[PDB]
Amino acid sequence: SQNRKLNVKYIVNGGDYTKIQNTEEWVASTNQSEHWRVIEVTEVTAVA
Amino acid sequence: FITANSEYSESSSFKNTETEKSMYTSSRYLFPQGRIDFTTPDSGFDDV
Image (cartoon, rainbow over all chains, first blue to last red; front, side, top):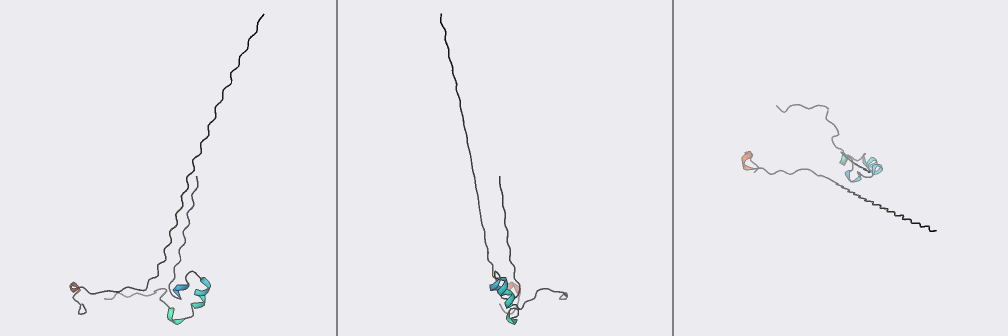
């Protein structure tokens, strides 16, 4: 008996998202302002 | 004055192999752009 399971997941948040499968090109695109996104939130205030 | 002889040799053999293989691959590329909302009259908002 034999079993094999493979699971691969890529996530992109900011940068050129069309370069998600090409790490080098995404790293090259990280300096473009038009693709900058919120990557974490360190303060949240209740709307009330 | 007499001699007699007899021999009987019998043999049986059996082999049975069963093989089952299964493979499945699932790929999903999800590239969102955002969300668009329409306003329902029950919301009470002026843009409806």
